[PDB]
Amino acid sequence: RPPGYEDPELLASVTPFTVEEVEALYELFKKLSSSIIDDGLIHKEEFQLALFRNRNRRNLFADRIFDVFDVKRNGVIEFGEFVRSLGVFHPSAPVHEKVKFAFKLYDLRQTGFIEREELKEMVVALLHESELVLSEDMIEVMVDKAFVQADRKNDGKIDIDEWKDFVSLNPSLIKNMTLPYLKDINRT
Amino acid sequence: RPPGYEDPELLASVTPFTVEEVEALYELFKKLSSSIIDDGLIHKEEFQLALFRNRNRRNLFADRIFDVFDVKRNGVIEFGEFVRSLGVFHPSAPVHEKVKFAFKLYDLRQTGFIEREELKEMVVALLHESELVLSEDMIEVMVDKAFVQADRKNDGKIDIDEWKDFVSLNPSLIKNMTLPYLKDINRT
Ligand SMILES: [Ca+2]
Ligand SMILES: [Ca+2]
Ligand SMILES: [Ca+2]
Ligand SMILES: [Ca+2]
Ligand SMILES: [Ca+2]
Ligand SMILES: [Ca+2]
Ligand SMILES: [Mn+2]
Ligand SMILES: [Mn+2]
């Protein structure tokens, strides 16, 4: 009848998941939040591991993932923060939540915008996802083309509205914003 | 005790598959070789369908796939041609067989080499696989860079040895040359 307890029905009701899936996602939270300290919290030290271990997204954006999972900005991931953040990568999660998330992900230094050197590191990391590693000058052409397409109100930075326009023409930037195993989950 | 009959043990023994898998791949051959004519042969007309239907590789290279599946060059795919050609896309199939196949695939007009305009249509089709559709001038830079890297003995055409060198530095050109469901198959 414990501390940190959250009725699964609660999460269930604000997310694509269901009670059983929520209940199931607790099992996995316990694993990740106990590796090193056992305080019902995922320390960033322990996010690394679980991502390095059962590989999900990517190593150099684990600080970026950890950062946007950390919704109530307080340095750790709690269970409901984790379930609500994972729920965004669900197949049926509204595309608004996906676009927004993906933007928070890319705003590398957390400043409310996406700046040209963050577009670049992004584009590099997506390209290397699809096994393409390109010349430094192939890259700043692409990054230049992308940046003036995106930066509609012409002022050196992409805001959440121009992003939304940009992504509507470039839907593969939010490709990874969905993980299709999350439709029915796999015991382990 | 029929015509066109081939002991499954036979195929089994020259391929990554096993008797049961061979036996299972017969079921699927019957489907594809009967759609339109029922002569135990896959006519190209019927290759199209099955690829348009239960999607595998890609629509505009279905003529290229059909062409290299057609090993004994006689205009149709027979059962053992089909099993031996599919067996190449298997996870455990030797990488020689994969590189060779991929080369036959790209030699678009069937001339024994890969020519610059075939490298180009290739690169375009791989790029569009990974959701990248690029400028016509981003493209001939890439295609130019790739073509002089590949065409070692400097003479306007890639042969099977320079290809082999090229692919060793570019292992993602043979990415699709493997299909991981073929490790244990899925009834339907
Ligand atoms: Ca902990
Ligand atoms: Ca938090
Ligand atoms: Ca930023
Ligand atoms: Ca037929
Ligand atoms: Ca044939
Ligand atoms: Ca050719
Ligand atoms: Mn702007
Ligand atoms: Mn050559």
Image (cartoon, coloured by chain):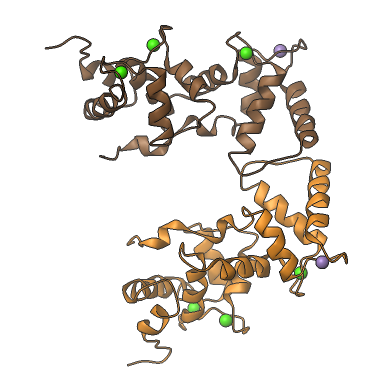
Chain colours: A brown, B orange
User: In the image, is A39 to the left or to the right of A64?
Assistant: left
Whole-percent x and y of residue A37?
29, 18
Would you say A140 lies left or right of B42 here?
right
Q: Quadrant of the C terminus of chain B?
A: bottom left
Residue in the image at 54% along x and 27% along y: A60
Residue furthest to the left: A1
The quadrant where residue A158 appears:
top right
In the rendered view, tell whether residue B33 sits above or below residue B127.
below
Q: Is residue B44 visible?
A: yes
Residue at left offset 66%, top offset 16%? A162
Tell me the quarter of the picture where residue B138 sits: top right
> On the rendering, which quadrant does ligand 1 occupy?
top left
Give percent across and percent down for residue B113: 77, 70
Instruction: Decide which of A88, B98 is in the foreground and name it.
Output: B98
Which of these two is toward me, B123 or B15?
B15
Residue drawn at x 71%, y 56% as measured from the top left:
B122
Image quarter of the N terminus of chain B: bottom left
- Residue A101 picture location, percent across and down: 50, 20
Q: Position of residue B34 (x, y in %)?
A: 45, 75
Task: Mark yes or no: residue B37 visible.
Answer: no
B132 or A53: nearer the viewer: A53
Q: In this rendering, would B140 be left or right of A36?
A: right
Residue drawn at 49 percent across, 68 percent down:
B93
